[PDB]
Length: 278
Ligand SMILES: [Cl-]
Ligand SMILES: [Cl-]
Image (cartoon, rainbow, N blue to C red):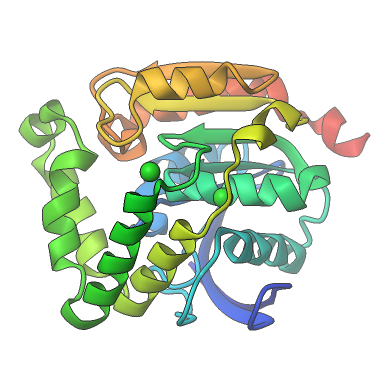
């Protein structure tokens, strides 16, 4: 892995990001969910790097990246991604993928950096903003995690993050996810919770998208259910919708091979070298 100070248009202007960068050629950036880290995309990074250059950062406040206290807006996280791509000399187009909060970041990136997208991968996410109660629950989480740490978040979220088959067949996956949550920096968790609460409604952004989009959801996702994600996909032009069987909210971890294959086959169609040159 790498750790670099990048220049970002968001406050505070410079931030240290930890990231993986594996493979050569056409760039695919994968953005983790809340309150996880870059390791949730490990299988896809390790497999897709035979064909693509896969960049997987820890977002501000997560994993090994710098923690910026206050509010970490989705826009700021997108600005950081643009700054990372700038640092790396990836100033043309990328494919940007995100899961859950990472999807929110992807929408913020599409708003501001549309000409930098060859494609979007939206996993287990939604375009609507938080409802008022959901916003308040963000704030409650933020205020508590600063003091108590994320154990209470793991307790609440783990049963909702993965399907029954994952608990049975892959207890090691459950434990990896649990350790991601338990290790998440408290002030980073708080800042991102507050940022999610104030994110805009991206519903109307979707019909205005101008790149191919893959929408992926676990069959048993309890947080962003497949029915809702299918409806979201029907608002996005040039979309492909895939349900991953026997996965909940975290298909990349729960059904890694199925996710890798879905992404690989779509990338082959959408993210070509001639498209990069011209
Ligand atoms: Cl957003
Ligand atoms: Cl909500």
